[PDB]
Amino acid sequence: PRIEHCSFCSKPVYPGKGICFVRNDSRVFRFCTSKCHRNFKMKRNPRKVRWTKTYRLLHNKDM
Amino acid sequence: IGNKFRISCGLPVGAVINCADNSGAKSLNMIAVKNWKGHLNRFPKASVGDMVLITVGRDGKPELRRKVTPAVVVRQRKVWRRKDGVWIYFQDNAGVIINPKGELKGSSITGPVAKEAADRWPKISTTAECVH
Amino acid sequence: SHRKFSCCRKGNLGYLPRKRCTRGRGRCKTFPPDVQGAPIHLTAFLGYKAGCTHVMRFIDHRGSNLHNRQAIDQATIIDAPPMICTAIIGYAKTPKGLRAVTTVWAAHIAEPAMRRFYRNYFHAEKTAFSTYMKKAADGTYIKEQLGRLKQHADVIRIVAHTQPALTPLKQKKADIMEIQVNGGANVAEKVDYAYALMEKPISIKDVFSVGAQIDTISITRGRGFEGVVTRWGVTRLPRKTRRGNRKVACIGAWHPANVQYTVARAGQMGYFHRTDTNKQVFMIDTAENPRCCTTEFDLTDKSINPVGGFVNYGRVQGDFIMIKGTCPGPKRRPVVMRNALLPHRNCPPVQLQWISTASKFGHGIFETVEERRQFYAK
RNA sequence: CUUCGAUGUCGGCUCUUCCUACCGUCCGCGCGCACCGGCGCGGAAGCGUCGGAUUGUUCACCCGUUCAAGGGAUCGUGAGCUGGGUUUAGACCGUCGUGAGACAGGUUAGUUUUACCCUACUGGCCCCGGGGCCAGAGCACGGCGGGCCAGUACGAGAGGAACGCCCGCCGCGGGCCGCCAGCCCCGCGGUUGCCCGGCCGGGCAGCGCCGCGCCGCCGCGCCCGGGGGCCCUGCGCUGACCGCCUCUAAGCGCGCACCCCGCCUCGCGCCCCGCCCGGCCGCGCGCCCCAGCCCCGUGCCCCGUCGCCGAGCGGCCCCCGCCCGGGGAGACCACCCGGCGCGGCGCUCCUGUACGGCGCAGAGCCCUGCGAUCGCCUGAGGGACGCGCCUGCAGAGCGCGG
RNA sequence: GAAUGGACCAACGAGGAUCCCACUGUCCCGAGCCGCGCCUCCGCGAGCCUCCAGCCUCGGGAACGGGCGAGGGCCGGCCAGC
RNA sequence: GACCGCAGCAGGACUCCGGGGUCAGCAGCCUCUAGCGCGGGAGCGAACGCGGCUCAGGGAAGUCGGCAAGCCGGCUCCGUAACCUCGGGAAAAGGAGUGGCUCUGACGGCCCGGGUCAGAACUGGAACGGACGCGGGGAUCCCGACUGUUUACUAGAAAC
């Protein structure tokens, strides 16, 4: 199906699941889960949470 | 214009919404919503794309304040569900001052504007930079 | 004096008395209009709620903003283990009202149906239809009784039993329903059609078609003794009130001297027979097919089972019917589906672009175990 | 006229019913009604009559909006509440009194007693099969816009309809949890003080605090809500009395958001079937019509008073367990299901990478020592009340009643 | 209205008003969740009240009846609420 | 723990001795010593109460009144207005920092002591008064200058 990924988590949001935030910079931020969103709204870094593909990239575990 | 699908109403009366247009008003206080029948004890409610009767806050230019003005809410902080299943929310709650005829009182609409607001009001749609 | 500000009553008095349903399962009560001119069709079928899901759909509703546009809706899967007919009941239309004119039972009644007859099968003496089996078996007696129905009956019904072995629940005893036979040119044809279905399985696919709308009947989810604020919808009074704010304040005037039945009072909320109506049948298929719920866009086999199993329900091994939105009742509860009595005229046509087999247990992102295995790989 | 060995007193909040002397919506009808809009009637009480600023306000008034009638219920509604008003004892001020004191003048501070009874109401119970059926009782969809129609009828223009269909929406109602919010029973991670010698792993601070969080419940989310019958006011039809005329006096058609039924919520009882299939009772049928009444005006007249055979119809009676364990169910019960459960293993999900070992990581310091941390083994480990299975123990009372 | 004291407010004040920023279930509009009661059991066990009796509608009556006149409902025995 | 209130009455009774840690603390929060397990227990986990938490978006629109709750708060360092009886206002308002580790300076006595105050690095999901303790703030108006006192048991006041 048509699929989008979390702007933070980088996991494919399945159709009908997730919340999209329109930032004041006119950028849509698609979020898979409430956890994906809460981490972003606390500005906690994506690259210090291991489950995120960003940290998977930094470890070079998944890139 | 057209028929508006119901969206969750996130801004009750007494809400203060930002101005998204260069009219010279900074903060708009929602006095009421157009087309509201009431139930005992129920404050009027409003959502993206709905005309709201607002008053300009003291921060606004003197000419704008001390009079009721019509406006359309274009951004809502509360998340709402579109028929396709998309749940969308905005960083801030904002509105643009517009006559019921549909003439904007402002040259430009700054920031993102909701698709629902843009379809219902034609002038907002051309002016808005982005319709996310 | 007067209420001063006009406010409506809270609650439907039609749904009073709000008591736990004494009838065991949701009963069909009234059945669809006979018509007297259609291929003979059974009008109902029992189901067990299996779960709910998301269905991507393409809308062809002309005149609506959704025309030529996609949508996602709540679906409700009703597990449908195939039912088997065990008897035929005929009803004369009498001045007093429809009254039975005798029923002819099957020569061989299945153990699930017999299990319904007893409270404890193991400790019972299994003495059910013992002399009946001897009276029939030859089957001459069954035909003679069926002939009595042909002359003395005007409304024909088929008794049917669900087999709960092919359903994840532990009911073990069968559920019996009188499914009406409607549409045949004449009563003699109706009972002839019934004899062909006797002691043989009926499947939802035969009873209901995709695109039709059905009325779902079941006992609602029970909340126990509830307060007036939850049960009837009243306001929680000002928080500066002594003795509580979760109570209707005044329950009547001086006169009438008695509390009226209108006034909201605290009691049992839940376990109420309710009939929902005109829920469109999105898809009828069997879970045995690996590609039963596949669509062109996903390109995966996609069986109806979510990853990890339906929640509070299980295998849904056999056929299933999917209804638009919701039906009354919790998961694992019998729900009688009946052909609509008043269908919605302007309903769109159902074309499902995608179905969700993502695990409903937790939040799912993978629609197959292989898909989740591929992501976690090493 | 009743009440003082006391019926708590104003207005609100909350909730429920009732009235029509009708504001809009519905149906006709008249205008000094072209359209639009107004206005006046008759029927009509289903639905709506809202959000707010001052005031204790009822009122009043003003602002908004789908533009917003008026009233009854011990001036509905205090073991329902509030105490704002009022209305005791404290205190000022103004006026009046020689004074104590007064005020139908203002100002502030000032306890809100008790239901366990009886009725009523709301649910729940008082052992008896499966399917059902219908007495009675409840009752529920209404309003508002848009798209067409059409800038068309209509009007000199300005303006400006409508039926029909199609879409929405708001209020209400009944559900539901797939999403998305909320929420966490003992899940995982962070962290502060203290204590268990430190590390690990814990406790205590009455869930120390925190960040997520499943099953479940929930609303802010979602599904759902299309109908018949007689008819009112009346509008018409054939048609008189009253050669005409005439909606009426017989006769006749249409017809209201009202009404009544349907669907729906309950349901005493009854029906059919099963296991059985046995007893008890009673003896009695034309039809229509009244301005043809087709031969009327009779008859029965004896349920014991001698009738009780049988057959035939029609009635009537007789049946139908718990405890116990779970749960989709629950105050208790009841309900629904039952050789359950316990605890494992897979699956899926929650949290976020376990202890420990390793490194030339590490700011530096100092001797091979120290070190908050960081990377790898590790999307790890830990947990689970959802699923699938038994691979282990088990699990169906000659317990009680019929 | 001028020591029946007048005007005057720095600083104070569990003194009496009005408004603003902030903040929040005060409210829209309620929802979930702990503990403890409640409920059920085991053991203990009162108080208060009490002509009698405890269903209604209307009528007449010390003008507002449970009882009286006329209807219309109603096995009896209990629980949790109210 | 036996007094006094009818009780083995969350009622009231005057002294004396007063350890450790966190701390400015005799505060709160845990503890050593010493005391000790209180007019009883089991279940269930309804409504409703009673205490306690959390709540999307809005925020007083609620109400007679922002009642109740929520905010704020420790320390250091900036930055502090009108007004004033020049003492105050003032903690005004309005901000910034705060943890752990690894160091480097200060400060005495005559190689021996203090553990407070600075200044760094480095590290951590964008965290640190991490519990606890602990002002929300401003603008006015009226009375009474003030600290005091007051109807034991419905007025704590502008009254005395």
Image (cartoon, coloured by chain):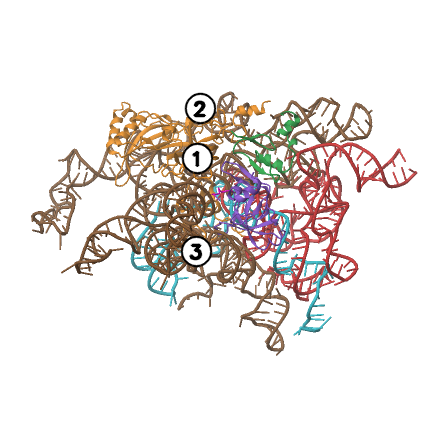
Chain colours: A green, B purple, C orange, D brown, E cyan, F red
| Labelled disc at residue C338 | none
* Number of numbered discs on residues: 3
Left or right: where does residue D15 sit relative to residue B53? left
Q: Give me the disc on residue C253.
A: 3
Q: Circle 3 — which element?
A: loop
User: Where residue B94 sits: x, y (%)?
Assistant: 58, 45
Q: Nearer the viewer, mark 3 or mark 1?
A: 1
Give the letter of the chain under mark 2: C
Q: Using the image, tell me which numbered label, if any, was put on residue C289.
A: 2
Where is residue B127 drawn, in percent x and y?
57, 43
Q: Which quadrant of the view contains residue C330?
A: top left
- Residue B5 within the segment the image draws in magenta: yes
Whole-Å distance between the Cαs marked 3 and 1? 55 Å
Q: Which residues are magenta?
A: B2-7
In-front residue for pair C2/B112 = B112
Task: Name the foreground residue: C4 vs B111.
Answer: B111
Tell me the CA gap for discs 1 and 2.
28 Å
Say what secondary structure mark 1 lies in: loop
- Same-chain status of marks 3 and 1: yes
Q: Closer to the N terminus: mark 3 or mark 2?
A: 3
Determine the CA span between mark 3 and mark 2. 64 Å
Q: Chain of mark 3?
A: C
The three-letter amino acid code for the residue at tag 3 is Ala
Q: Which residue is mark 1?
A: C60
